[PDB]
Image (cartoon, coloured by chain):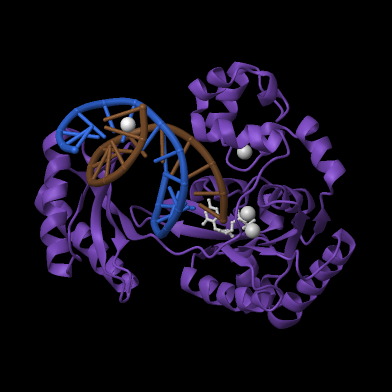
Chain colours: A purple, B brown, C blue
Amino acid sequence: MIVLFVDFDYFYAQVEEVLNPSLKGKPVVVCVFSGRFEDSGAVATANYEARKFGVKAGIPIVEAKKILPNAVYLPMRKEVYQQVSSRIMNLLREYSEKIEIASIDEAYLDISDKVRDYREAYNLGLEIKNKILEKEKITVTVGISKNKVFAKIAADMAKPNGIKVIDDEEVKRLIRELDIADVPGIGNITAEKLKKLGINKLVDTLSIEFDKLKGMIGEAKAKYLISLARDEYNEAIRTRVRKSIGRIVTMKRNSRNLEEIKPYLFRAIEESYYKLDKRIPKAIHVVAVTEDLDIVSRGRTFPHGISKETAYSESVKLLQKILEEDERKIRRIGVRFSKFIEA
DNA sequence: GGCTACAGGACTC
DNA sequence: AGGAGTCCTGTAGCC
Ligand SMILES: Nc1ccn([C@H]2C[C@H](O)[C@@H](COP(=O)(O)OP(=O)(O)O)O2)c(=O)n1
Ligand SMILES: [Ca+2]
Ligand SMILES: [Ca+2]
Ligand SMILES: [Ca+2]
Ligand SMILES: [Ca+2]
């Protein structure tokens, strides 16, 4: 198989530049303001000019401002970024029937039937980049390889505004040489667990006892890494269908008082139901983030769809369970709906 | 022994 | 010390 992966560069920040070209060449930081106090919140992303100085996704906005007090700080406008995303995805559909939209800024295309070899794949990648630049003035990075995982790795290597093929010989090189932390699905927690076992490369997973590997990282992750290391990985490129919709908000102060929390919970429900738009969930989960940043939840599945009135009443019962079973104060409160009726 | 539903761990964006 | 969404797993009831 020949897989072509597209990952949009500096996406939210790049969109803001397209809509305001005066931002060109300035550091730009897209922010998620929690509303708790002045500049409370985190960075969603930043462009190269800010990121090169350490302003990276997830850091507190106050910390970004200590590093770059004169950068341009913009509130996240996700609805804008989504609309631009959708248009770019529509452009990509023209290059393959076999296409997976993986996230707000990623797609995988199976181009096995559109091209013969990696040379033709590379050239199609150039054509795609040109098209997206022509139509939307957005730069992207293309990764091309034999499966989804190595196509994503290919793009990681070529970012930003790049294009890279990882041929069959380089897959073997990477199995030996790629830091296993840089494999998709391996975060800091798993990477450290693997270091405890002595595993630094994919190849290392082949010689460790399977039960040892599994005991530390679980069966699925073990089999995943081994299949990659064996160069025997397969994962379908296919239509992702949204399985859950939800909203969680930060409260102005921490609280374990039901009547103080209800209004935030009810706003989260209202916004969630708006986003559901015709989709009818059969399951509801209430999610709380405690003052110490632990996430706790309580959910329920019904044998029918959940009306908004039922969501209100059941959400309170689930929050009640959290308050009954946990003595801590709550900082963020929200809901997630799932198990949609197939309409 | 392996379904199911639920609560939490961990990852991606 | 944001916020959205997904997949896996330990546990316990049930067959
Ligand atoms: N922790 C994160 C990571 C990404 N995002 C959003 C903002 C990013 O522009 C897009 C795409 O993620 P990606 O990790 O590829 O980041 P960039 O494209 O480099 O900005 O998703 C976010 O809101 N929070
Ligand atoms: Ca990506
Ligand atoms: Ca990106
Ligand atoms: Ca990693
Ligand atoms: Ca059995």
Q: Residue at x 57, y 46 (%)?
A: A66
Q: Residue at x 52, y 72 (%)?
A: A82
Q: Quadrant of residue B13?
A: bottom right
Q: Is residue A261 left or right of residue A140?
A: left
**Is residue A133 among the parts visible in the rendering?**
yes
Q: Quadrant of residue C5?
A: bottom left
Please state the horizontal and vertical placement of residue A130, each as a whole percent of the image. Answer: 80, 75
Farthest residue, direction right: A119
Please state the horizontal and vertical placement of residue A113, each as a whole percent of the image. Answer: 75, 68
Q: Nearer the viewer, residue A220 or A77?
A: A220
Please state the horizontal and vertical placement of residue A140, each as a whole percent of the image. Answer: 72, 65
Q: Nearer the viewer, residue A103 or A230?
A: A230
- Classify A116 as above or below A295: below
Q: Quadrant of the N terminus of chain A?
A: bottom right
Please state the horizontal and vertical placement of residue C15, each as a whole percent of the image. Answer: 19, 38
Q: How many marks?
A: 0
Q: Residue at x 26, y 62 (%)?
A: A268
Q: Nearer the viewer, residue A235 or A149?
A: A235
**Is residue A20 among the parts visible in the rendering?**
no
- Classify A143 as above or below A134: above
Farthest residue, direction bottom: A135
- Classify A192 as above or below A283: above
Q: Residue at x 24, y 57 (%)?
A: A283
Q: Quadrant of residue A121?
A: bottom right
Image quadrant of ligand 3? bottom right
Q: Nearer the viewer, residue A313 or A231?
A: A231
